[PDB]
Image: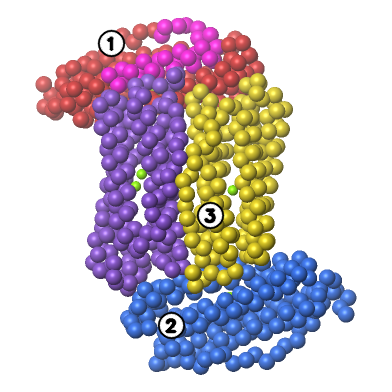
Chain colours: A red, B yellow, C purple, D blue
Amino acid sequence: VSQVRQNYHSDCEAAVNRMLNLELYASYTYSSMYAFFDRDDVALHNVAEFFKEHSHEEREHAEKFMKYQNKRGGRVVLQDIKKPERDEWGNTLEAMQAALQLEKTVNQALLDLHKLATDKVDPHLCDFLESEYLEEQVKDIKRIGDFITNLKRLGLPENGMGEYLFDKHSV
Amino acid sequence: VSQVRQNYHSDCEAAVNRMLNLELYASYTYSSMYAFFDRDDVALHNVAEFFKEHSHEEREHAEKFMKYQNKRGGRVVLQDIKKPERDEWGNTLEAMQAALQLEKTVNQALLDLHKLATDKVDPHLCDFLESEYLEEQVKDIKRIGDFITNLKRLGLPENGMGEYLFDKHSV
Amino acid sequence: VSQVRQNYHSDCEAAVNRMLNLELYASYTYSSMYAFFDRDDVALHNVAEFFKEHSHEEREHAEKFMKYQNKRGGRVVLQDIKKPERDEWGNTLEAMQAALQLEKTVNQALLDLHKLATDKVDPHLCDFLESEYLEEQVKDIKRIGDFITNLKRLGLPENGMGEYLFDKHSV
Amino acid sequence: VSQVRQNYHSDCEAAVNRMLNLELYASYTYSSMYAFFDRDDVALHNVAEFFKEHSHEEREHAEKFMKYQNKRGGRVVLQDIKKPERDEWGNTLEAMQAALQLEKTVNQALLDLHKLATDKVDPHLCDFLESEYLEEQVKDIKRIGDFITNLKRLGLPENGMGEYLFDKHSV
Ligand SMILES: [Mg+2]
Ligand SMILES: [Mg+2]
Ligand SMILES: [Mg+2]
Ligand SMILES: [Mg+2]
Ligand SMILES: [Mg+2]
Ligand SMILES: [Mg+2]
Ligand SMILES: [Mg+2]
Ligand SMILES: [Mg+2]
């Protein structure tokens, strides 16, 4: 074992490695959504940049976990990043709803990892999660929630003008 | 009595204390409206900030009355601030209409206090009301009136896109 | 329920709404103390501003809870803000002692809400309390404690010159 | 009559001339108080400057009335300025109490002149009084009241150290 390792449980380490991968998956899913709205037959470019920013963020989150792992004397073990669930994302409402579920999935995983850290009595990993991840996630969930509400206000599945305006005003 | 008190009628003092409380009530009602539009299922954030600004204003008005009271040798006597009449405010039109009534209620109370001050021949309280409150109130009533007219132009109870646009342009 | 809500217990939500109100009560009590020292027959103006600052702070704390609530998908439900316990606050020592009890009451309520959040396994609300409230409270309790000690050193209930000096040096 | 005169009653004019003189009297009384505290056996120099500032203010008030008079087509008629009531003013508390009475006397005279202007239906003189004099007077009465309270807190008739400190901190 690492000469640095202290109070770092094996399960925690494994869960962090798992979380890292989920982060890269989420990043990759947003990369899909970016490419979808950049398409000429979809063309909502501000929506597209919103998702591109988000893929970069989740990628930076995954790297923070890599750094974390090594700080604690754990070892990074990477797995395959699975392709996102869809190839086309429908429209802005459909994509935002997909995004809300993706963020709640990631949020749940983080809460779970927090509970594991609490059970294994690792104060440091608990703080890492609280400080770098948990508030960031409710911020993002609240923002996407707000977007879905406003997309629906604009009567989105059907109203094209509403979707166009959302691109020019909410992002 | 206060060594400072001069030409300050007992009724006026009591009415000022009453007015102070009405101001805090109005402030509290706007605080409700702020929280309502900040909700994820309501999400009109500029409307929400409009009302948040207004709660801060009515609170600053209440404090001006506290200061006034002591300047004149009167004594502040606080009462309970009653919870606002509604918990949910419907939509932007419904909330603006509620706000217009609330402002006319406050305006009426101020005009009443002015009449009392005129009857008791207190030039100083009359000027205080004229200078710090009366013009501010017709400004606000005219503004909210304008908003209601524009909300209706946007066909508001029913038109969601109209409500969204109001949030991006009128506030 | 809120599309945003995740791991947010009903009890927690209710307790947050309760805490919000306690904050507004504390704010209102300080508003009393401000008006008391601004009186011409009391006239300690720096003490008065100290309490006025504090009412603004507790009001900003209440608004943070409103924001919090909506971030988590909870719903703000406001109650009446009860008038403060006294109308006159005696002297600077008496008011500071009242303030120390008020702050320990608020502190206790916060610690309680933290225990509830820990029992319901809500890491996010726990962090919110730790980060925005708990340290702020021991800072304030320690400061008011220091003031009471110094007020007593100045032999306060009886020594008027001591009270005057406190106003010019400790605030 | 003045080609400029319009809606300016003869009584009002006479009362303004009277008020002017009262202002110069008040100014002269403060000039006494200034000279008293500048004495080597009294030596409270900040108290002395406070009163010197105040004599300059009441003199500027008298000149505003001269200007007013001519603006309205009235004619200034000056009278003798009577010497102040005392030659020595005792101590800082005694002088402040004298000052509080002097200011309430002036305040009363102004309120009276306002009532006369209201009876003669002169809106312009009423506004002049409200704008340039009435608020200034309650500000000053509240300030001197505060001083008397603090002088008494310092146990003034008897406590010399309290008087010294007041000079270094309240003015
Ligand atoms: Mg993430
Ligand atoms: Mg995220
Ligand atoms: Mg108001
Ligand atoms: Mg208003
Ligand atoms: Mg607090
Ligand atoms: Mg506090
Ligand atoms: Mg004057
Ligand atoms: Mg004056």
* Foreground tag (3 vs 2): 3
Query: How far across and how far down the image is residue A155, in percent?
Result: 60, 16
Spatial CA span between label 1 and label 2 = 85 Å
* Residue D29 position by quadrant: bottom right
Secondary structure beneath dot 3 equals helix
Residue under label 2: D92
* Label 1 residue near ligand 1, CB within 8 Å: no
Question: Which SS does the magenta portion mostly show?
Answer: helix
- How many badges with numbers are in the image? 3
Question: Image check: A96 left or right of B115?
Answer: left
Q: Residues within 10 Å of mark 2 (few under 14, many from 20)?
A: many
Write down the chain letter for disc 3.
Answer: B
Q: Residue at x 54, y 72 (%)?
A: D140
Q: Position of residue A82 (x, y in %)?
A: 35, 8
Amino acid type shown at disc 3: Asn
* Magenta residues (range): A84-112
Q: Residue furthest front?
A: B11
Quadrant of residue A117 within the rendered picture = top left
